[PDB]
Length: 66
Image (tube, rainbow, N blue to C red; front, side, top):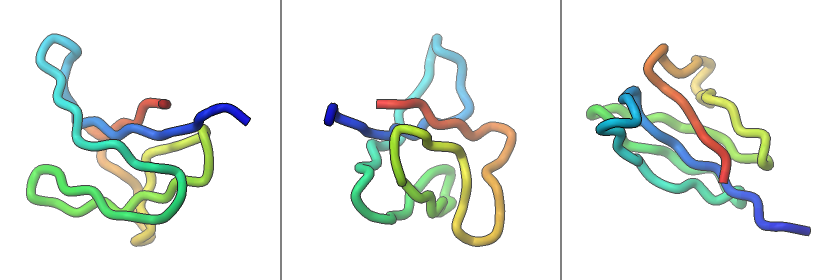
């Protein structure tokens, strides 16, 4: 029973990337980026850019593990 966590970032090269915020895999919350609100869902280590508003993240949206 290791530690599982999901992270969210914004479209930006690793040269000047910028972390948005950490999302604990315990409840459903919303993220604020580019004056927009992205409501993602965390179920486990397997996290994928998706919204609960019947829509999918943009082309400049991503989500790394941990």
